[PDB]
Image (cartoon, coloured by chain):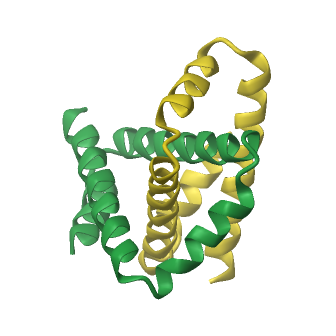
Chain colours: A yellow, B green
Amino acid sequence: NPLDKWNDIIFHASKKLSKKELERLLELLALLETFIEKEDLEEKFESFAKALRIDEELQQKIESRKTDIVIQSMANILSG
Amino acid sequence: NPLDKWNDIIFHASKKLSKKELERLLELLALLETFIEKEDLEEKFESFAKALRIDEELQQKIESRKTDIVIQSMANILSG
């Protein structure tokens, strides 16, 4: 449901603000991915990622992180 | 303009497919951020990021990476 609210805000904000926020996220993703390559960590990331299907603790940490991202995102849009 | 096409596809695909794709990206961002923390790389990432305003070469690499992300994203939506 926090994620539903994020989607609501994205799709109902002005096209100008939603576009800027999604581009911000795209750029951050690109930076992060590029950093991981620059530092040769790709295999390590991949392992760490598989865990999510099974590991309850990680699932909790990622879920908490996604909400933090949503909150920032929402703020950015409301902030203008 | 590649980014405009991404936005077009996001906002004009079914709400079901666009929501799933944006959630996929959110989860990936959360994984990446969490990984960087788990590995104590936060300061290093931050420096690497500042460069983007000035460094032509990085600007090119990130720009190429964003397009790759867009292409995958678009494919995901078209793929269903």
- Quadrant for the N terminus of chain A in the image: top right
* Identity of the residue drawn at 63% across and 44% down: B30
The residue most toward the bottom is B54
* Count of residue discs: 0
Q: Nearer the viewer, residue B50 or A12?
A: B50
**Residue A65 on image: x %, y %:** 73, 45
| Residue B23 visible to the viewer | yes
Q: Nearer the viewer, residue B19 or B42?
A: B42
Question: Which quadrant of the view contains residue A34?
Answer: bottom left
* Identity of the residue drawn at 77% across and 40% down: A64
Q: Does A27 sit left or right of A48 as displayed?
A: left
Q: Does A13 sit left or right of B60 as displayed?
A: right
Q: Nearer the viewer, residue A8 or B29?
A: B29
Q: Is residue B11 above or below residue B34?
A: below
Q: Is residue B56 above or below residue B78?
A: below
**Residue B67 on image: x %, y %:** 27, 60
Question: Which quadrant of the view contains residue A9?
Answer: bottom right
**Residue B15 on image: x %, y %:** 38, 45
**Residue B45 on image: x %, y %:** 63, 61
| Residue A66 visible to the viewer | no
* Identity of the residue drawn at 48% across and 78% down: B52
Q: Nearer the viewer, residue B32 or A6?
A: B32
* Identity of the residue drawn at 62% across and 18% down: A51
- Quadrant for the C terminus of chain A in the image: bottom right
